[PDB]
Amino acid sequence: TRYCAVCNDYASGYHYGVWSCEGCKAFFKRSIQGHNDYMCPATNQCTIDKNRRKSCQACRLRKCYEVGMMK
Amino acid sequence: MKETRYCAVCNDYASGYHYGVWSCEGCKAFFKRSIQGHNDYMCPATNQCTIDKNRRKSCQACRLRKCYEVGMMK
DNA sequence: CCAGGTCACAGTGACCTG
DNA sequence: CCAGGTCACTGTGACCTG
Ligand SMILES: [Zn+2]
Ligand SMILES: [Zn+2]
Ligand SMILES: [Zn+2]
Ligand SMILES: [Zn+2]
Image (cartoon, rainbow over all chains, first blue to last red; front, side):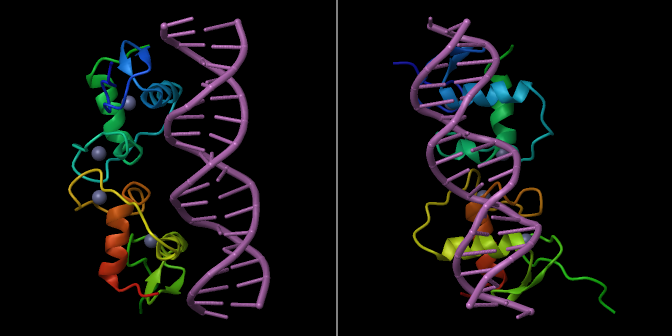
């Protein structure tokens, strides 16, 4: 029992370099294909979790990189 | 004197006066859906998000909050 | 006018393919 | 096993209807 390094949902495998859910995986995936900068609605410290992850993409991506994800 | 109207909620161009405040089509539809039943809205931060035109799709909780704050009434 | 409907559209994530 | 694809679902907001 492994948990997403990004949001802590249950991981599905080791994706882009860390343990991660299908959600963070695909998100990260989408991200590297090109995207306008994201915007945090608050102060750049959101709580990324299983639910809240859909809300702050900016924080999600940041956390994506922080925990390691890379192509 | 006033050249334009702005959305009391998000500050984007207002389109009419909906739910009792000048509002954009976005905030109007948002509020509409929200009053149409139970809502599980969450804040990803501390319940003090900035709702503007770019951050509006981001926190539905705070958006609703301001909807009510500024006067919207069903 | 406005309220409430509608629907093309974009992000999402579970699941498939290779 | 995984990366990268797919696509059913869902929330949005621009528009329409009554
Ligand atoms: Zn995750
Ligand atoms: Zn954030
Ligand atoms: Zn608005
Ligand atoms: Zn919020």
